[PDB]
Image (cartoon, rainbow, N blue to C red):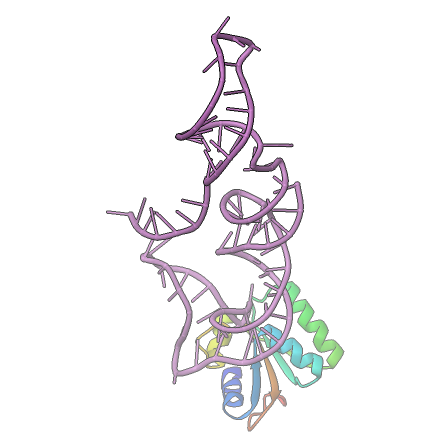
Length: 95
RNA sequence: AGCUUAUCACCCCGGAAUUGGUUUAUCCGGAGAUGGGGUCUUAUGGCUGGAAGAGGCCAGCACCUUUGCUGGCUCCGGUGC
């Protein structure tokens, strides 16, 4: 269950929301996992994948739109991409 | 004609729930709000050149007359379903 794993990292780990801040984290090497919404434009999705290739960052594709991804991270606004800086008690990186 | 002048739009920094901003009219923001600093269109307005030498309003003089001559002032504001 990705929703339960993603909910746990919010309460303990360090995360980052939004496209502009995610690219900054990948550029600095601080990112460990990126989650992309289903309805993200392909050109933006293609650019994010290219950035993760250069920094050797694992990419996960969320099975839902930006409305659904925002709910999973416990926010009342749409989220297009989520960058995980470091996990806490969750094992999302090892699953 | 020169300088300058803008709602909208756009850029940089930054990263938002204790949701904020905002129109008479409810729309916008992690696809990046509010905020701080910038860029641009010149509708339009301001100052200056054009240009006071013009035009306007008066006063004092010549005189059949071709008809003129000499003087001053022409400034500074307010208001709107």
